[PDB]
Length: 227
Length: 234
Picture 1 (tube, chains in turn orange, brown):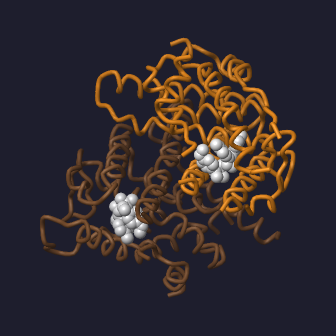
Picture 2 (cartoon, each protein chain N blue to C red; picture 1 turned 90 degrees about the vertical axis):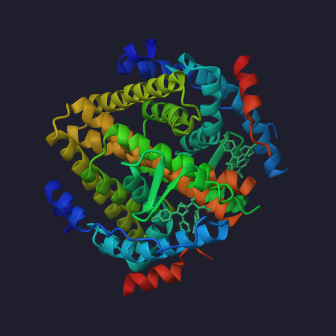
């Protein structure tokens, strides 16, 4: 796979080039606007995912499983990235900057978790090159432990995913070493960034929990991938 | 004193703190009903929770926190901690979850409860991943401690900012310990950081299993804040 031959800078360059644009809110019903926004973001997310090195080496069934498990975490981590420069606020779009008081509409509990994630990123001085690495880890990791098959192909697919995840780890480390971090600082920061992904999983599970609907089904994702 | 520990002293402290393995209620009526299986598992978990507080109080740095923050971390982490212990106990039993030495269950037995074959399958996949990574006991105790300190830290004045900093400093210390363990084992630098990432990434899966375990549940057996607090003071 081409992905496994990439250097750290080529991997970063590929991911930076795949970044979807920042969409605007069309306009009210909170769910209304957020739903309209997320629906337009998902279309760009499928095209982004097709451009993550290694992803299209997988079967369509496995690409859908990964997206089904990761899509809300991917939307949330984009939101948190957008919001770093707005302490106390969530920048859903450039024309939809919501503060905490506008979550009281069980939405506040998740707003708070999202704000805490944005704060953490700010604290850490999270860089854009690191963000795109983290977003692609979410895509490949979130669903990998729940492939439901035991065929040779499934084993080969999971093994490919883990080698791409290793490549992204190497990339994260190279970015930090090139920024001047000591060997120990490199390990510590890699771990800090990966541990935040556990909180993003938690937030996504909450959001799903309170929802239960408007979730993209397996069949919906398969068709968007086929097009 | 916790941040002054060497990597070597950290592993020795975590290994010494480690809780006993408990038995399920002896000679339960078999085959199980959904209610009787949930009864056995709840009784096992309730007894394990007592020893989890004892272990937690011995995790370097945990007891430097206020009691409130200690309870908050245990409330957030308790089921994840129980599940990683289950996954570890079960590594040497493919196809099977060793809930206790006298309670080894195969996948068909997870079907007795509604929706708990799904989780049951998720736990089996984790034990297989640990088996295939050949996870070592010293790594397991570091990972269980990371879960305790990490799961609740992002859901907490200067005092609060200092508590979090202390937690992130202890987490760094446990990270350095994991790396130290992999270096002494002979892993290249590249292999060290890749293995660290692989282990930390499995923790997001454990979070997912704990979340689903709760959701299925809700579809009073959870330990209360007051209960956790009472056990921490005694």
